[PDB]
C-alpha cells in the first residue's frame, strides 16, 4: 500500500466522518481533532509509517469540500457514508 | 428493575434504532427483526427474565408511533437518537 494510498484512505474516512458529524446528525461522533487522531490510530494499528497529522488534516479538508460540493442529494450521501464508515466508527469508539 | 421497566427500556431502544434506520439514514443498522433480537440480547446480558419477543415488538411499535407523531423537527430527533443509542448500537454490532 503506497504512502499516497495510505494518506488517501485515512483522509477519506476522516472527511466522511466529519461530514456525517456535521451534515448527517451524527452527534455521537467526536470533534474534528479526535476524528483526525482516530484515523491516525487506524494507520498505526495497520503498522503504517507515521502519517503526519497536519498533512492528513489538509488532505481531509480537500476531500470534505469534494463531499460537500457533490450534487448527490444529501439523504443519499448520508445513507452511503453511514454504511461505509460503520467499521471506522467502531474503531474510533 | 421491574418487568414493566425492563420491557419499556428494551422497547425504547428498539423503537429508537428502527427510527434511526428508517428516518435518519442509518442504513448501517440491520432489519427490524434483528434490532428486536439485539434488544432481547441486551436484556439477556443483564440477566433479565426472558422477555417475550412479540410483546417487545408490540410495545416497540407503540413507541415508534410516538417518535413519529412527535412534532419536534426531524434533525433534532435524529441528532438526539444518534447520541442516545450509540451504546446500544455498539452492542448490536
Image (cartoon, coloured by chain):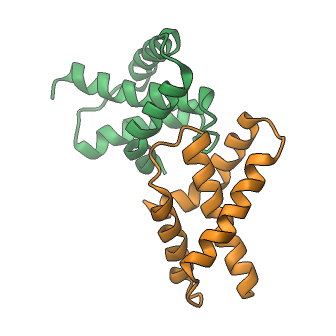
Chain colours: A orange, B green
Residue A46 visible in the current orientation: yes
Residue at 58% in and 84% down: A51
Number of numbered callouts drawn: 0
Q: Residue furthest right?
A: A71
Q: Nearer the viewer, residue B57 or B17?
A: B17
**Which quadrant of the figure contains the N terminus of chain B?**
top left
Instruction: Please say if A93 is above or below B37.
Output: below
Q: Nearer the viewer, residue B10 or B87?
A: B87
Residue B36 visible in the current orientation: no
Pinpoint residue A46: horizontal percent, then vertical percent. 57, 82
Pinpoint residue B79: horizontal percent, then vertical percent. 48, 33
Q: Is residue B54 left or right of residue A48?
A: left
When asked about the image quadrant of residue B3, the answer is top left
Pinpoint residue B88: horizontal percent, then vertical percent. 40, 42
Instruction: Please say if B37 is above or below B73.
Output: below
When asked about the image quadrant of residue A61, the answer is bottom right
Q: Residue furthest bottom?
A: A49
Residue at 60% in and 47% down: A20
Instruction: Please say if A92 is above or below B39.
Output: below
Pinpoint residue B33: horizontal percent, then vertical percent. 55, 32
Residue at 57% in and 41% down: B29
Q: Is residue B41 left or right of residue A29?
A: left
Amino acid at each position: 500500500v503506497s504512502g499516497q494510498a495510505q494518506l488517501e484512505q485515512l483522509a477519506s474516512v476522516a472527511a466522511g466522518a466529519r461530514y456525517l458529524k456535521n451534515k448527517c446528525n451524527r452527534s455521537d461522533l467526536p470533534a474534528d481533532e479526535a476524528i483526525n487522531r482516530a484515523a491516525i490510530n487506524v494507520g498505526k494499528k495497520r503498522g503504517w509509517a507515521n502519517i503526519d497529522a497536519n498533512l492528513l488534516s489538509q488532505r481531509s479538508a480537500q476531500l470534505y469540500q469534494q463531499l460537500q460540493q457533490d450534487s448527490t442529494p444529501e439523504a443519499t450521501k448520508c445513507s452511503q457514508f453511514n454504511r461505509q464508515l460503520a467499521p471506522f466508527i467502531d474503531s474510533l469508539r
